[PDB]
Length: 213
Length: 204
Image 1 (cartoon, rainbow over the protein chains, first blue to last red):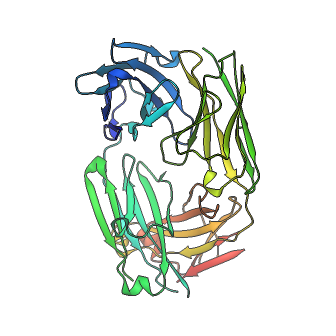
Image 2 (image 1 turned 180 degrees about the vertical axis):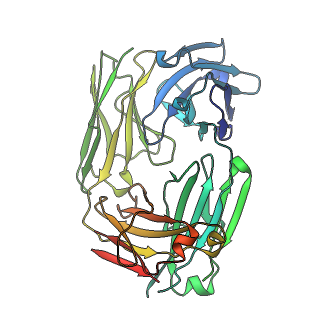
Image 3 (image 1 turned 90 degrees about the vertical axis):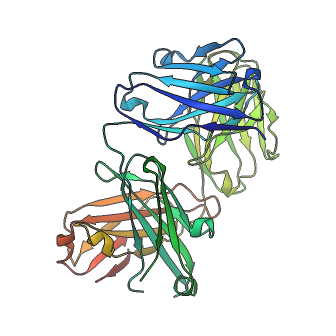
């Protein structure tokens, strides 16, 4: 299968210099044009430029002519994206994509770049049980005070999909706060064992919080 | 730099209805245009290429028309899982450019939320801070007011609201309202309540 693995979430300070990577597998990048795209929170797609690994040739959307510098290593099947003089304006999700020449048939999972002075901080995870209360039973998880984005939240380690709602994080202070809700039938909550799993890679934090009344 | 004007910015239709999205290029791109679909927190997925060709795995109800400088994406029989943002991209010449996109939403039938107020936790209280999260789940339309009442009155402290994107299955929206407080400020008053417009749920 054709895949494109991108480097992990990165938090760096203003004025720094980064170089994100996009590693191909299942095909040879020497054969395609690879592209880089930027996408800010709840906003559109913006191409930065592309490269032809064969000869090393590149072309950039003029907006990025002095911000970005795309490179490739045919040996390692890897494409890079360098961004200099970082500002908060550069904080966003970056994607690499293969261009067959008719469309973009493969996209990397994307890399989350945060430009800020804030320090990495693990979240606290507080279970949210009813405490009062009946056909349905809703309970939630509360991920408070982590930085930078993002965090992932699962229940029973993946088991139980529907009846799930994870709300987008908001800045409660210098940090992020996020909540998630699950909805299992009455008989379950009690007897069963409902837990939420949190992952905050940026601080190699993993946590499981068993719900309790 | 060939510019791409995409239209409309956002729109809604009821299931079954058909929507048409358009993109116009600043010059003739000779059908070297493609459409994409992007759902929330997800990467984009190719929909059409060469103006009219469907991509693999893509349904029939998605079709592309136009030529020259004018192009359009038509989705005939609208499905609740069609909620997303669509982008056109032109490769008539480098640098290639995307349209500003169209945010498409499903126009279903009114639906009241399912509220669930939650009391701060001990571990949280273990730290000088308390939060009272309220969940308003699966409702439509998306707009809604959220009011909190400490005991019987409304006093300033701190409220934060977060909405999920539209549901692929039932086409509803969900929101969380979290009342923030300092531990000791919480250990005073007694009847906390979150209202929605009314609808109420509370605890002592």
